[PDB]
Image (cartoon, rainbow, N blue to C red; front, side, top):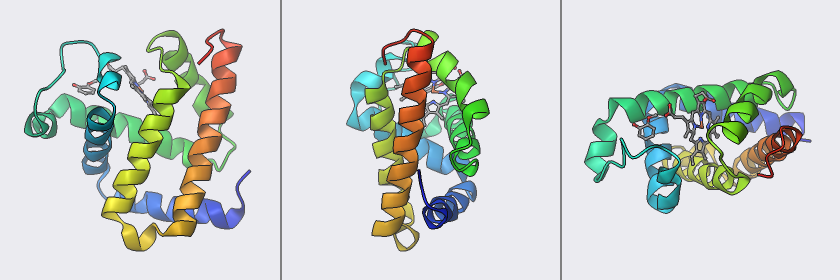
Length: 153
Ligand code: HEM
Ligand SMILES: COc1ccccc1O
């Protein structure tokens, strides 16, 4: 459980993200695919774009980054009271996309990386610690939902 002050640091930097959701989403997904190429296998071969410039030019990738960050932002704004937002996400990611918790740790690391790269003055140690706690809680609760659906994460 996060304190109210930790939630405030999470949501303070998230408002910075919302100034350019598409740009952040592009940076986060490109960082994920570069840091962990295997994650690009969960998306079908139709992509597997070969260069960074192709990734940045991809309207499909940009639109998807917005979809991802919008869902995460909706969850974060619930400050832990997120069962109703999290359940459909767990359903699709356990039973259709088959995304292990390990991959959620990878994308959390990418989120942290891009937030620090773009917003260092609003993402010092206490804000990094609060975002880390928020994403840990997200991953814990989604793992529990995964198991409830029969997916061992
Ligand atoms: C913060 C973490 C994440 C959030 C909030 C998120 C959310 C979503 C949302 C809202 C969609 C569209 C609706 C749906 O099917 O549920 C989606 C699609 C998808 N997501 Fe995730 N997701 C993340 C974790 C991941 C990771 C780590 C991978 C791959 C390693 C992944 C790849 C999947 C795939 C494969 C689709 C279908 C894409 C397509 O339309 O072809 N996601 N995601
Ligand atoms: C769903 O579309 C994409 C997601 C991630 C990377 C490239 C894409 O076209």
